[PDB]
Amino acid sequence: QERTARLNELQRALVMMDSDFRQIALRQTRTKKLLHWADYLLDSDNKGIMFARLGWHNPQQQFPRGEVTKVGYRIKDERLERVWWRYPDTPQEGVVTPLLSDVEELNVRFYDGKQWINEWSNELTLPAAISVELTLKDYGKIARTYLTPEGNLQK
Amino acid sequence: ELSQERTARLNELQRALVMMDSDFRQIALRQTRTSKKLLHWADYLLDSDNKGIMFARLGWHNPQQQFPRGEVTKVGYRIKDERLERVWWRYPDTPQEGVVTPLLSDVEELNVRFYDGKQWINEWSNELTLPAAISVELTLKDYGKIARTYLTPEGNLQK
Amino acid sequence: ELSQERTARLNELQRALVMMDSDFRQIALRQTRTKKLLHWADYLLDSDNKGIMFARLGWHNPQQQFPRGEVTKVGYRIKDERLERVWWRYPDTPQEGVVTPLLSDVEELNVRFYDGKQWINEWSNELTLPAAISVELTLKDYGKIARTYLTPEGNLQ
Amino acid sequence: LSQERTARLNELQRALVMMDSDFRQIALRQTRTKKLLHWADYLLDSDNKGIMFARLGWHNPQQQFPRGEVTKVGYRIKDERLERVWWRYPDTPQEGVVTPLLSDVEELNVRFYDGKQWINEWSNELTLPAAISVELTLKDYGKIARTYLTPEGNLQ
Amino acid sequence: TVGYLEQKMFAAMVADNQMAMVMLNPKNLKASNGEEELAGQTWYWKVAPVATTQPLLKAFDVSVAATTQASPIITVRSYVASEN
Amino acid sequence: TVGYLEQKMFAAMVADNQMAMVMLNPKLKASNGEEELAGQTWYWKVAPVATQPLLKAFDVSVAATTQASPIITVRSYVAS
Amino acid sequence: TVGYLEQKMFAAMVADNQMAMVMLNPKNLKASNGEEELAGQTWYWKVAPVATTQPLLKAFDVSVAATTQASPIITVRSYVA
Amino acid sequence: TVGYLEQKMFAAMVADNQMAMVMLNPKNLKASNGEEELAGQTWYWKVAPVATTQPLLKAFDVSVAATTQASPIITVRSYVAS
Ligand SMILES: [Cl-]
Ligand SMILES: [Cl-]
Ligand code: NA
Ligand code: NA
């Protein structure tokens, strides 16, 4: 009953996170970095993460060929919430989706090619992989590893 | 007081539109079963209380090494008890109940029209090509009719 | 003695075909003057008989640059029973091109166009390319040889 | 004299068009006789240095996999002539299609840009140099050079 | 606050619908105008080509207003490949 | 029903995480390991699959023990 | 030497021509055969589906021979999505 | 006729060479100028950013002339993404 609804809530959370973290855009955002990962980012109660993501491809004729949006994840009162902005450059409150309840912790790690590390300060390239770990009050720790698009920016 | 509930409603709608933008702008030229179709559009599809729609969509690009380049997922929309719900499947060919998202409450109707190059028509039975454009209209209890028009990718399948 | 002349002719033929593959496999859905996708008419390019002209993909530009590809323009013609290939850097061009003499002893250049059910002898559709093109050369020594090339999909509005 | 000097220029334009077609389309794709760029004395039986690399030949029709057809080309000097050699397949057992491109070329030289400077050799087998300079010393005109940019990316 | 937010969201919806119509046939980019009913309200849209200082991209503006005379609630600029 | 659906979801998550690690450097060998997820140890296995010269294939399979049949097997392809 | 070189080159042209015809409509990929006149010679071509270790790609071989019995001068393999 | 055609073709080679160097590092689009010897002649090149009305494309001109004062033999304009 509750357990099935809880499983379904988790399923939805994961689909959403897949949609965002598998579409990280190699594009710097302001406050400027490729990946923002810091205590109280987005008014998170703990860690917050923010990045640009591929929104959709535009129709054939249109330039640019795709529209980049900006998304973030934070914990607010032990809920995982996802924040959405139409524009990577934004003056603004984002569109908040409460994604998953009973999330104590959000942790993200970064693969630097040889090992997992805890911060990402390189603003010219993405880490080759990102690991998003959630600690749930019921199920405990679950994690997802995602690959990033290859490429470098210039200084 | 009540201005809080109206803000929450507009916030709900913004969320719904973002989700629909994500889906309808990324429609894929990929036939799905249920005899296959490019776009499924019928009364009671997916157990809708009225119309339902189902289609393949670009879910994401896979990392450069990987073939195929695009991962195609499958999504649909239906009304259940005046709720717009979005249904999602990881694979376009699925035995599997879908992941249901309650997207928008107080939606009476879902109506979709297809641009066939000269008119907007009420069904799509061309299995070889998508319509050039799709108009998705919702009838909300409070706001009435609102509509979004989306363009599809160009291309033909072989017969 | 003139095992050498036969070998030279074979090698010449080989060079012509690599060059034609290069052009005909890279036809671009882009209209040219003097407005067609594919020009196929008598005395085109001052050919002695039929001449053919089209836009082609010249190369991809480096990552940073827009547009991502440079489109060039090419033509084939017969002058004094020799096949010649003409090249222009720019599809829209004010006159004469860079001329490559490609193959001697060509009696006839003919091109045909596959409209999805059969082969026809002209292409007047200014919005779409034909699914396939067949280029037929009649050599005085070898006779008729033909190459079929597919075009990119898509139409212009 | 006007006729002959006009014919020489047209010969050079022809050479340039052909070289542009090759060197602007270098493929990040290793070849044998593995290297990305082959650059060595007597390569392809050159009188001096020879250069060889994989290049994009053409895009295949949209149904076909792979989307790109990769060919292999090389340049050498044979008896003060620049020759272009062409192979349909990048992994070829031996003789390529030879085109005499430009007469009275005394030297072919190739330099490689490493992001900071021009250098004389390229022994990185996983990445291309960001730029390549092809230098021809013509018997009449002296040195003419074209710089080309390569595609970004690394192999493992 | 909510009345203004409504206007902004719904006028943006109309802007998107009219951008899409222009994009169906962007070789035929010209000054045009009309009306769309959305959320009970008539909205007045205008498409306007934008002069460019290059040959590669064409631009147009789609603006949406509450009357035929009114300043727009929303204006959005888009770009179309001139040689797609 | 819910306990089976849990096993399915959590093994699929480990399958995805391990495919990702394969894809990081596929130039591809048989390997295996253990990932702790949702309080359970999952036993994964990467296996090359024979194929044409263009694509490499691997299967990722995840089981509840080293002896057990897999709960899930996913196949992926990599460009040669 | 040139006699063999001619055969190789002209059989290869027929292979390319018949591949292009398969590529035009490869959903109806079937075993087929026929004849092409090229450079004064009849060439005997054959199209053969090839099994593939995956659902994504289909393969075919195009082979071209001097008779209906002969071993091919040329066999080319191609893949379609 | 031929002297003229030499200058056109050789200035054009230098234009292409210098555009290539700009394209290597185009975020750093600033005015520059220099010299290139080609076919025995010193050519004077100029790189000039070109004002733009849109936010998507940056533009620049490469011009090549026979002296530092002379009007250019050739000017080529190129566009770069942001
Ligand atoms: Cl999405
Ligand atoms: Cl080429
Ligand atoms: Na004859
Ligand atoms: Na000298």
Image (cartoon, coloured by chain):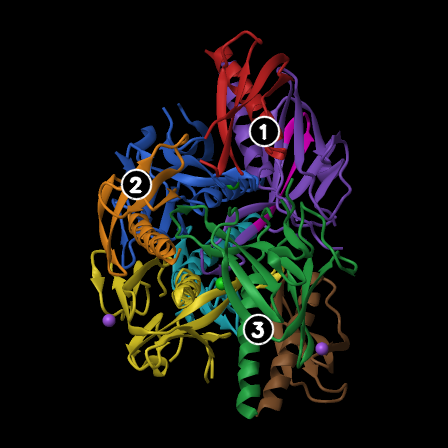
Chain colours: A purple, B blue, C yellow, D green, E cyan, F red, G orange, H brown
Quick check: B60 left or right of D127? left
Q: Which of the chains bears the disc numbered 1? A: F
Look at the image and tell me whether residue C152 can be seen.
yes
The residue sitting at the front extreme is C1
Q: Residues within 10 Å of mark 1 (few under 14, many from 20)?
A: some
Name the secondary structure under disc 2: loop
Residue picked out by circle 1: F28
Foreground mark, 2 or 3?
Answer: 2
Tag 3 subunit:
D
Q: Which circle marks residue A29 in the picture?
A: none
Discs 2, 3: same chain: no
**Residue type, numbered disc 1:** Leu
Drawn side of residue C145 relative to residue D80, left or right? left
Q: Do labels 3 and 1 share a chain?
A: no
Quadrant where the N terminus of chain B sits is: top right
10 Å crowding of disc 3: few (<14), some (14-19), many (20+) = many
Asked if the residue at tag 3 contacts the one at tag 2, i.e. Cβ–Cβ closer than 8 Å, the answer is no
| Residue G15: image location, x then y, percent | 33, 50
Task: List the residue tagged with mark 2.
Answer: G71
Looking at the rendered structure, the secondary structure element under dot 3 is strand
| Helix, strand or loop: magenta stretch | strand
Boundaries of the magenta span: A68-80
- Front tag of 2 and 1: 2
The structure residue drawn at horizontal position 56% and vertical position 10%, both measured from the top left corner, is F64
Q: Mark 3 = which residue?
A: D102
Query: Residue E53, position in %: x, y?
Result: 58, 75
